[PDB]
Amino acid sequence: SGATRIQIALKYDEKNKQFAILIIQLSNLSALLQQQDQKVNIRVAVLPCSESTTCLFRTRPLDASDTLVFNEVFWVSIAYPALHQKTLRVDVCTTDRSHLEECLGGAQISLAEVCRSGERSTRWYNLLS
Amino acid sequence: GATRIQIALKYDEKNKQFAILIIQLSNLSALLQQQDQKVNIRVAVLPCSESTTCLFRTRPLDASDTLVFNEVFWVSIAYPALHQKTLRVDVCTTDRSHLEECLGGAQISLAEVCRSGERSTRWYNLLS
Image 1 (cartoon, one colour):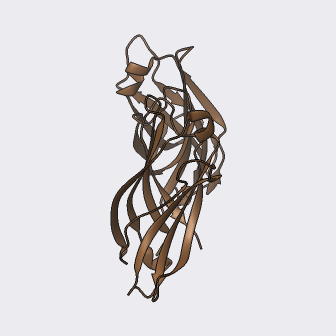
Image 2 (image 1 turned 45 degrees about the vertical axis):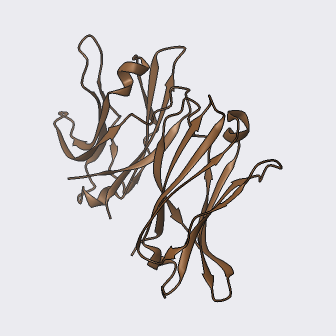
């Protein structure tokens, strides 16, 4: 196999001064989670946390699979100068028995490319352990 | 694997200028086995506008599995016209008579290009 990839869309709306993070789908989860009787969630964090609005989001948990479809958007009330300098950390995290959290891989993503003009960027990102 | 090409796209709106930076080519050996020949990149802004320049070529460099072209192309075009265009990049081989036969390429959408000017760097697979 290859690496585990995750597909995400990014769009910034300056009228309403908010940022959209759409977690679309995960691919090749087997590269990170070999035994798959667990449920995984995508953990999303806008770093630095910023000491005002929610910086930590988490998808619903789904039964592991090598083609896993979350259609969860998260909105964050931010302005472009702040946003433009931030980092997006995403991790595929599972939970073992007794709701413990363990994260199997992730990626930090520069937002310097996010478009102030509001165009959507849709890319695949590799999650490394 | 597959021959990949890394490209960055930035749009200047004060001026009406579009920048296409051909950055590098990875796993060229997936398309060109005999790497003794020389290689260049062909780039076309489609639909090719008459009364405008649309086709471009990089300098020809000796075939490497990892080959860095560091070569920008500038186009005079506006965002409305840019927004419905498509980019055709092919990896081609040329000899000294400048006979060009192309080994593969890809069609790239410019719907993500930022009008605000933010650069967009990405890899693309070149297909046979």
